[PDB]
Image (cartoon, rainbow, N blue to C red; front, side, top):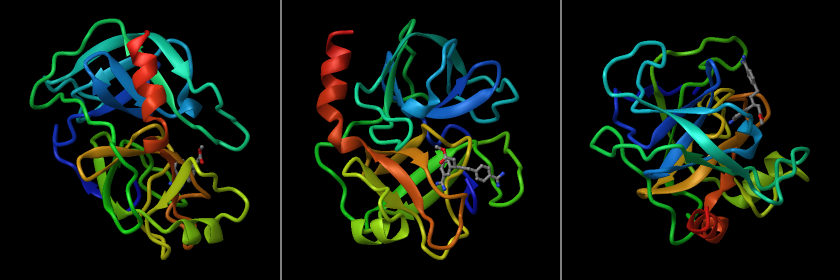
Amino acid sequence: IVGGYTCGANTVPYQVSLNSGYHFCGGSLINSQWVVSAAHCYKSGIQVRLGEDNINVVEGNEQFISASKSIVHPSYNSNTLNNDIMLIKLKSAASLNSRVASISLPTSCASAGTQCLISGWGNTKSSGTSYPDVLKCLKAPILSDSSCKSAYPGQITSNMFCAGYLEGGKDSCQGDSGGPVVCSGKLQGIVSWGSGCAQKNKPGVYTKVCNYVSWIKQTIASN
Ligand SMILES: COC(=O)C[C@H](CCc1ccc(C(=N)N)cc1)c1cccc(C(=N)N)c1
């Protein structure tokens, strides 16, 4: 997260870190046994880490649970990043409390101008590199699809939205991938892609979760 603030330990209780020996992507706990992330975060040997603040220090609230299966969206295209979404089932159900809670799926899509909270442990610089140990947060509005398409000619599909600031300076980044965009108490987006980070006229592009709610509900009902 470039240009954000320190969340505060366990203030974003649905945030997960995906670990394969190290943090490589974020994710969102949507129920006691399922996490949503970006399909571009797929790999084997994922351990889901819940209840994290400092991902390098065991501080007491963590639950480390291995994934039993992962399901990449049937129509995911890695070249265009269309349908960039994936479900991960936990080997055991998490224990849900105040510090570890699920986030609700949307009943409807969010409108341009809606304020959102994006979080993750990704890079905090646009040109340089510096990875935080603790969780970073950013409030950012959903942009109009017109401005989104103007910024990224020929690249924005119906399964994508932009959020952030056209002036730059504030954005998600590498390492934040797969993580939550929560608006109005609902998971509306997944950190997906962008040109660089926090560059002028290049906002963050996010998987449009409201388009996938049926697929998500149907998949977890049979798996
Ligand atoms: C699918 O992945 C991507 O699009 C990658 C890309 C980051 C590439 C990058 C890597 C390192 C650095 C740096 N060290 N300063 C900067 C940019 C990316 C990933 C997630 C969000 C955003 C976003 N703009 N919201 C951008």
